Image (spheres, rainbow, N blue to C red):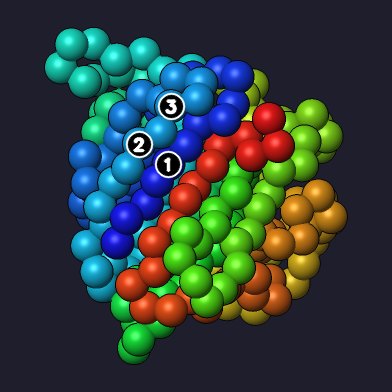
C-alpha cells in the first residue's frame, strides 16, 4: 500500500512511520513546508502509525532529538514516538478490509487529515487548534498538548483495568476533534476501507 505524506504546515516536520517493532519504509524523513513523501507499507501490516515530529535536530548519522514525537533519537524511526503525537493509525488487509483512524490517546502536536486516495470509504480529520486551546495541566512545554494518561498516570486515564469512562480531559480532545479517538474506550471512529486501499496523510490540512 502506498501512503503519500504531505506537509501543508508552514513549518518543517519530520514524518515518522512505524509498526512499533520496526520501521515502515525508511521510518522517517524531513518534510519542509509543502513537501511530499511517498512510502510503501507492506500488505497485512497491523498496528502501523504515521505521525509528525517537531523541532528536531539530527547529526550526520541520523541521531538527535525532537521536541514532540521523538523515536529514540533516530531520524529513521523503528519504534513509536514520545507523546504528544497526533496519530494516523492503520491495520491493513485484515480479513479483506483495511481499518484506519486518527487518535489523540497519545496527545496532539500537529493537525492532520488521513484520507483514502482510492474508492470505497471516507477520510478522517483532526485539525482544530488543540494546542492553542489545551488545558493548562496538559500543555507540553516542548510543544503540544499531552493526553491525561501521559501526564497523570492513573488507571482511569490509561484504561489500565479495561473499565474506564470518558473524563474531563478526554472530552476536551473529543469536543475539538469528534472524529478522533479521545480515550481507549471511546466509541470507535475507525473507518473501514476496502482491503489494499491507498492513502494520504496531510499535516496542517487547513493551512
Rounded to the nearest whole Å, what is the CA distance between mark 2 and mark 3?
7 Å
Q: CA distance from mark 1 to mark 2?
A: 5 Å
Q: Pinpoint residue 64: horizontal percent, then vertical percent.
A: 30, 18
Q: Quadrant of residue 78?
A: top left
**Disc on res. 37:** 2
Q: Quadrant of the N terminus?
A: bottom left
x then y, percent, for residue 4: 40, 46
- In the rendered structure, which disc, 1 or 2, sits on the residue that comes first in sequence? 1
- Residue at image position (15%, 17%) is 61
The tag earlier along the polypeptide, 1 or 3, is 1
Which mark, residue 5? Answer: 1
Q: Tell me whether circle 1 and circle 2 mark residues in contact (CB < 8 Å).
A: yes
Q: Quadrant of the C terminus?
A: top right
- Check disc 1 and report its element: helix, strand or loop: strand
Q: Is residue 193 left or right of residue 78?
A: right
Return the x and y of residue 88 as percentages of the image width and height: 50, 53
Residue nearest the observer in this picture, 163 or 65: 65
Residue 149: % across, % down: 61, 51
- Residue matched to label 3: 35
Are the residues flagged by discs 1 and 3 in contact, CB closer than 8 Å? no
Which residue lies at the image location 55% right of the left edge and 54% below the top edge? 114
Neighbour tally class for label 2: few under 14, some 14-19, many 20 plus, Cα within 10 Å? some
Residue at figure coordinates x 60%, y 49% from the top left: 113
Q: Are marks 2 and 3 in contact (CB under 8 Å)?
A: yes
Q: 10 Å neighbourhood of mark 3: few (<14), some, or many (≥20)?
A: some
**Residue at the image point whose x is 68% and y is 49% from the top:** 126
Q: Is residue 71 above or below residue 32?
A: below
Picture layout, residue 32 above or below residue 146: above
Nearer the observer, 23 or 140: 23
How crowded is the residue under tag 1: few (<14 C-alpha within 10 Å), some, or many (20+)?
Answer: many
Quarter-of-image position of residue 65: top left
Amino acid at each position: 500500500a502506498t501512503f503519500e505524506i504531505v506537509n501543508r504546515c508552514s513549518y518543517t516536520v519530520w514524518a515518522a512511520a512505524s509498526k512499533g517493532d520496526a520501521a515502515l519504509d525508511a521510518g522517517g524523513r524531513q518534510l519542509n513546508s509543502g513537501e511530499s513523501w511517498t512510502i510503501n507499507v507492506e500488505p497485512g501490516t497491523n498496528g502501523g502509525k504515521i505521525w509528525a515530529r517537531t523541532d528536531c535536530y539530527f547529526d550526520d548519522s541520523g541521531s538527535g532529538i525532537c521536541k514532540t514525537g521523538d523515536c529514540g533519537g533516530l531520524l529513521r524511526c523503528k519504534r513509536f514516538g514520545r507523546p504528544p503525537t497526533t496519530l494516523a493509525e492503520f491495520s491493513l488487509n485484515q480479513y479483506g478490509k483495511d481499518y484506519i483512524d486518527i487518535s489523540n490517546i497519545k496527545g496532539f502536536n500537529v493537525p492532520m487529515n488521513f484520507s483514502p486516495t482510492t474508492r470505497g470509504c471516507r477520510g478522517v480529520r483532526c485539525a482544530a487548534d488543540i494546542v492553542g486551546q489545551c488545558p493548562a495541566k496538559l500543555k507540553a512545554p516542548g510543544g503540544g498538548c499531552n493526553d491525561a494518561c501521559t501526564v497523570f498516570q492513573t488507571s482511569e486515564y490509561c484504561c489500565t483495568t479495561g473499565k474506564c469512562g470518558p473524563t474531563e480531559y478526554s472530552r476536551f480532545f473529543k469536543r475539538l476533534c469528534p472524529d478522533a479517538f479521545s480515550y481507549v474506550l471511546d466509541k470507535p471512529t475507525t473507518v473501514t476501507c476496502p482491503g489494499s486501499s491507498n492513502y494520504r496523510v496531510t499535516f496542517c490540512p487547513t493551512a
